Image 1 (tube, protein in one colour):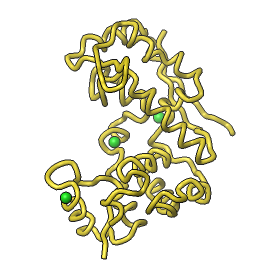
Image 2 (cartoon, helix red, strand yellow; image 1 turned 45 degrees about the vertical axis):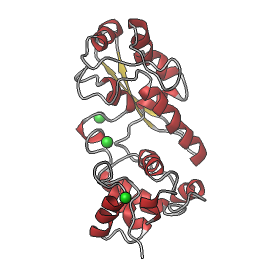
Image 3 (tube, helix red, strand yellow; image 1 turned 90 degrees about the vertical axis):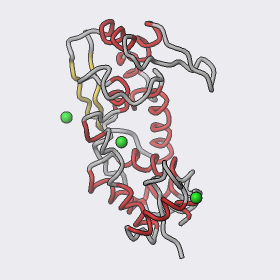
Amino acid sequence: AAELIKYNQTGMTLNQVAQIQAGLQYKPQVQRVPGKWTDANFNDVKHAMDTKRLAQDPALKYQFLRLDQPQNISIDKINQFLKGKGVLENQGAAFNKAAQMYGINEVYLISHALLETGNGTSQLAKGTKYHNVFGIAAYDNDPLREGIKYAKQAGWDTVSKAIVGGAKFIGNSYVKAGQNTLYKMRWNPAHPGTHQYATDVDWANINAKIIKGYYDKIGEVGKYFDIPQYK
Ligand SMILES: [Cl-]
Ligand SMILES: [Cl-]
Ligand SMILES: [Cl-]
């Protein structure tokens, strides 16, 4: 209703910040066609980074949405969206709960739950059964039994429960270390070339697309934004 946007003027310049990306040892990629990367040129990075262009686009501005800020989306609105999503069908309540506890945007938490469980169909989320809607301890030895093992250990015997305990894990490493918007996660304006999430120059733009997609399904729009400014 009343978007609240904060603008941080580095006083720097897009020309400076983009060439800085080009000197990184972990060189940037460009999926000109899906499934294949190539290093991006100065224009490729300067365009993908140009917040002036990303702020004007309704799907692209979501990279500036603050992920560390819960929005009070109605729990009913959430279930209308979680409907039919395998397990997780209900419990937007368990989700609003994980959101207010850790101070983290709700859509960021749910899309993350949706990816790890394949929209509620993952065996780990499927769960007598213990559950895991966040892939906790699942990227190492045995993703299925090792994760079932974690969930069994913390009492995630029910879906609202796997959601509460898995939630503390989301955003500590990125959203809580200051990279609170998909743009900061990609370009890191406080420390450029530092702690960046991926080489693809389109990574905040793609993720902004999927987020705004969930916002539209859900029935809401973002309210807290943060746009870096170069001049
Ligand atoms: Cl702030
Ligand atoms: Cl397994
Ligand atoms: Cl994170």
